[PDB]
């Protein structure tokens, strides 16, 4: 990684990838990775394996989808973070687990957890972009409330 925009590409093992400043792309590959966007607007994709994703400050994009395993987002700041899930919104479940938000793809064991979502706004992502539609924070909370009474 460098202060410039980098494309950081892991391998099938457990990799640590730190983007540093600049608007980076982090592709972990298989294995259980640690990905840090740091400063800047970063795109993080843990891919297969159970990954820890730290977008950092700035407006970060997290990818998720079928076969991505159990990944955990640890946010730090930014008013325009996004999760881009390669599935229809009609296949997403939302639940509060402790202080975390858990997002599941129905029919799979792929699960994305936002650590400490419910602690304060700096831990949150602001939009979920599914294949067909976008869901904002008020929308995510309505889904969590609806799904908890399901
Ligand atoms: Ca960066
Ligand atoms: Ca960089
Ligand atoms: Ca890897
Ligand atoms: Ca991985
Ligand atoms: Ca960042
Ligand atoms: Ca961020
Ligand atoms: Ca993963
Ligand atoms: Ca945020
Ligand atoms: Mg700064
Ligand atoms: Mg782990």
Image (cartoon, rainbow, N blue to C red):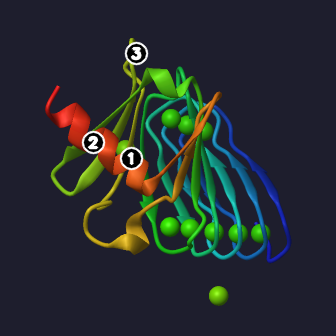
Q: Name which residue lies at 47% across and 22% down.
A: 90
Q: Are marks 3 and 2 in contact (CB under 8 Å)?
A: no
Residue 36 in the image: state x and y as whole percent. 58, 62
Q: Are marks 1 and 3 in contact (CB under 8 Å)?
A: no
Q: Give 63 or 79, whichever is nearer the viewer.
A: 79
Location of the N terminus by quadrant is bottom right
Binning the other alpha carbons within 10 Å of mark 2 as few (below 14), some (14 to 19) or many (20 upward) gives: some
Reading the chain from its start, which is encountered first: label 3 or label 2?
3
Badge 1: residue crowd in 10 Å (few <14, some 14–19, many ≥20): some
**Mark 1 residue's CB less than 8 Å from ligand 8:** no
- Decide which of 4, 113 is in the foreground and name it: 113
Residue drawn at point x = 43 percent, y = 36 percent: 50
**How many dots with numbers?**
3
> Label 1 belongs to which residue?
140
The answer to whether residue 59 is above or below residue 92 is below
Circle 3 is placed at which residue position? 108
Percent of width and height locating residue 31: 53, 34
Of labels 1 and 3, earlier in sequence is 3
Q: Write down the quadrant of residue 131 in the picture.
A: top right
Comparing marks 1 and 3, which lies closer to the viewer? 1
SS type, badge 1? helix
Q: Is residue 67 left or right of residue 131?
A: left
Secondary element under disc 3, as helix, strand or loop, is loop
Q: Which mark is residue 1?
A: none
- How far separated are the C-alphas under marks 1 and 3? 20 Å
How much space separates mark 1 and mark 2, taking CA atoms? 6 Å
Residue at horizontal 71 percent and vertical 67 percent from the top: 41
Do residues under tags 1 and 2 come within 8 Å of each other at their CB atoms?
A: yes
Residue 144's disc number: 2
Which one is closest to the eye, mark 3 or mark 2? 2
Crowding around mark 3 (Cα neighbors within 10 Å: few <14, some 14 to 19, many 20+) is: few
């Amino acid at each position: 990684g460098s202060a410039r925009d980098d494309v950081l590409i892991g391998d099938a093992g457990a990799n640590v990838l730190n983007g540093l400043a600049g608007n980076d792309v982090l592709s972990g590959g298989a294995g259980d990775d640690v990905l840090l966007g740091d400063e800047g607007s970063d795109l993080l994709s843990g891919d297969a394996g159970n990954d820890d994703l730290f977008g950092g400050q700035g407006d970060d994009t997290y990818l998720f989808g079928v076969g991505y395993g159990h990944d955990t987002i640890y946010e730090s700041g930014g008013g325009h973070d996004t999760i881009r899930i390669n599935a229809g919104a009609d296949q997403l479940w939302f639940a509060r687990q402790g202080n975390d938000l858990e997002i599941r793809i129905l029919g799979t064991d792929d699960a994305l957890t936002v650590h400490d979502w419910y602690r304060d706004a700096d831990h949150r992502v602001e939009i979920i972009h599914a294949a067909n539609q976008a869901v904002d924070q008020a929308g995510i909370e309505k889904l969590v409330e609806a799904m908890a009474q399901y």
